[PDB]
Amino acid sequence: NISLKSKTNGSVIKLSDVANVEIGSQAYNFAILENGKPATAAAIQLSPG
Amino acid sequence: SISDVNNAIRENNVEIAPGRLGDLPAEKGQLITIPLSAQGQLSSLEQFK
């Protein structure tokens, strides 16, 4: 419902009329299989010494 | 003014961000990804004049 000020006729349009708003991931780089099924994981690297 | 000579160079000698074509929040059935870029800057003396 963030209102946008049109420049053609001076209307009042919301954000949902020119876009699509959803909850999604921040970056879409990596994905993980584990046995053929989608999951997630984290890789742990040990310190020097 | 000299602030107008400075602003004319910033508009006309600009660095455009490259991007890709087919980045990973993508459609279903996309086969080819390819980088894209645009030459925004100037190169010689004749363009600067």
Image (spheres, helix red, strand yellow):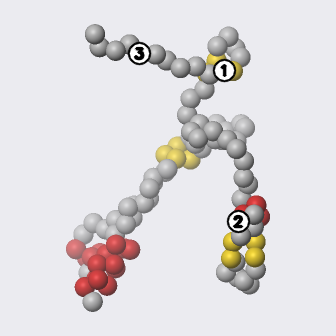
Q: How many C-alpha atoms fall within 10 Å of the one at disc 3: few (<14), some, or many (≥20)?
A: few
Label 3 sits on a secondary structure element that is loop
Identified at 58% across, 19% down, the residue is A41
Identified at 59% across, 36% down, the residue is A28
Q: Chain of mark 1?
A: A
Residue found farthest to the bottom: B1
Instruction: Tell me which numbered mark, 1 or 3, is placed earlier along the sequence.
Output: 1
Q: CA distance from mark 3 to mark 2?
A: 44 Å
Q: CA distance from mark 2 to mark 1?
A: 35 Å
- For marks 2 and 1, give the one nearer the viewer: 2
Q: Which residue type carries mark 1?
A: Ala
Identified at 49% across, 46% down, the residue is B35
Q: How many C-alpha atoms fall within 10 Å of the one at disc 2: few (<14), some, or many (≥20)?
A: few
Residues marked 3 and 2, same chain: yes
Q: Are marks 2 and 1 in contact (CB under 8 Å)?
A: no
Q: CA distance from mark 1 to mark 3?
A: 20 Å
In percent of width and height, residue B8 lies at: 34, 79
The quarter of the rendered structure image containing the C terminus of chain A is top left
- Residue that carries the numbered disc 2 in the rendered image: A2
Q: Which residue type carries mark 2?
A: Ile
- Residue that carries the numbered disc 3 in the rendered image: A45
Residues marked 2 and 1, same chain: yes
Instruction: Tell me which numbered mark, 3 or 2, is placed earlier along the sequence.
Output: 2
In percent of width and height, residue A12 lies at: 75, 76
Q: Is residue A29 left or right of residue A45?
A: right
Could you tell me if residue B24 is visible in this image?
no
Q: Which residue type carries mark 3?
A: Gln
Label 1 sits on a secondary structure element that is strand
- Residue that carries the numbered disc 1 in the rendered image: A39
Q: Chain of mark 2?
A: A
